[PDB]
Image: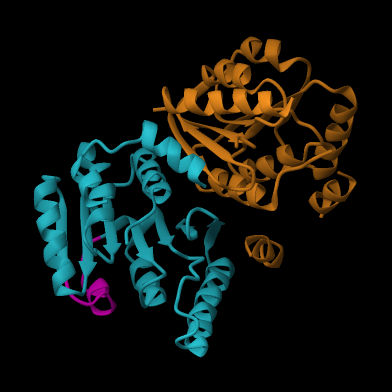
Chain colours: A orange, B cyan
Amino acid sequence: YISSKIDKYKELIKEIEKDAVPIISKEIREYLKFIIRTNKNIKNILEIGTATGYSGIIMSEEIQGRNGTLTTIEIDEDRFKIAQSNFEKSNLKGIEQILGDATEEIEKLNKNFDFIFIDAAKGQYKKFFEDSYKLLNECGIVFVDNILRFKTIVKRLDEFVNYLYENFDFVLLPISDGVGIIHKP
Amino acid sequence: NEYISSKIDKYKSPNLELIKEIEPIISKEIREYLKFIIRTNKNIKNILEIGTATGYSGIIMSEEIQGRNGTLTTIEIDEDRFKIAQSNFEKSNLKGIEQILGDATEEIEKLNKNFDFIFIDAAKGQYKKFFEDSYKLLNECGIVFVDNILFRGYLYKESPKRFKTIVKRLDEFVNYLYENFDFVLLPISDGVGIIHKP
């Protein structure tokens, strides 16, 4: 029902889709855009795992007005070059791409952010959360996607949800495959 | 999801105890989300609530604004629901609570007050009148929360023509917010519409 509405109401974006690699939901994308558009205080964004740059682009589009900057790190060199040629095509301003290891790069970033996108389906989410949460201004948001071999990935994911609830201002949302929002007081 | 609900039990049990004692009311998923939005926006100071009922949602949201000396205006049309709500607010000791007894189709436009946050239940009323009259009292950057926006729990057999009338209005209201407002649709519980005002 909701995707019918988003397609109904909510172009290079359309074609990064078809070539894709997994990308964010229509539902996540639209909520992402909402959160960022409606808090003019989100000026500086960190994204862990550029992938194809689809998520980086739809986040950066929203912050163009307030001259926001998007800092995004990606390990894979192929996905980097692809994301980099999409960022160029989008003509968006303020995008800082890094090709490296986020596990080492986050702490060596020596600046702060208002908003952090971590994808839990993808790599070392807790190490990124713990590293990057220190880099988050007051009143800042970490958005954690896909938060809700298999049986051991599900154990660690359940342990991460409990760990946030025990230590952070945290909501669990049943959007798409799970959205975990943490707010920093 | 029972999973989320199960996590709310372990970690987000209410600080007020009267709340657990009052627990049709909002989902526990809806309660924590509501609670979360209000807490993380220090600019949410005055709340408009259209549909007091037993006063459970009112306590829920008002508990998040005691720190700010925030207020809560809340309208209810049914005398009996009103008196229950008024008993519960008293037991709550929460400050800032203003109850209005009357019809929100008339009462909303009469308020000389401004609001940062409006709660409206699309499952119960003239929700579009409520939305258009109340949105005018909404400060810039304010939020309208429309609960039960994806609701489809209505007696179908008793009158299918009435069921299809109700749902068609809802659907045309979703379309209306999309075409005209900063709107987001969220599949939480029975459906949540959030409208931001610039």
Tell me residue A34's x, y (percent): 56, 49
Question: Image point 21% across, 74% down: which residue?
Answer: B77
Quarter of the image for residue A74 reads: top right
Left or right: where A46 falls relative to B113: right
Question: Image point 56% across, 43% down: which residue?
Answer: A36
Q: Is-magenta flag for residue B110?
A: yes
Left or right: where A9 falls relative to A74: left
Question: Image point 48% across, 26% down: which residue?
Answer: A162
Tell me residue B142's x, y (percent): 39, 54
Question: Image point 70% across, 31% down: which residue?
Answer: A121
Q: Is residue B18 above or below residue A118?
A: below
Q: What span is in magenta? A: B101-113
Residue B120 shows in the view: yes
Left or right: where B90 falls relative to B114: left
Q: Is residue B112 above or below residue A73?
A: below
Q: Is residue B68 above or below residue B46?
A: above
Tell me residue B147's x, y (percent): 42, 61
Q: Is-magenta flag for residue A161?
A: no
| In-front residue for pair A36/A104 | A104
Q: Is residue B152 above or below residue B19?
A: below
| In-front residue for pair B53/B115 | B53
| In-front residue for pair A178/A128 | A178
Count of numbered circles in the view? 0
Left or right: where A24 falls relative to A30: right
Residue A40 shows in the view: no
Tell me residue A169's x, y (percent): 41, 30
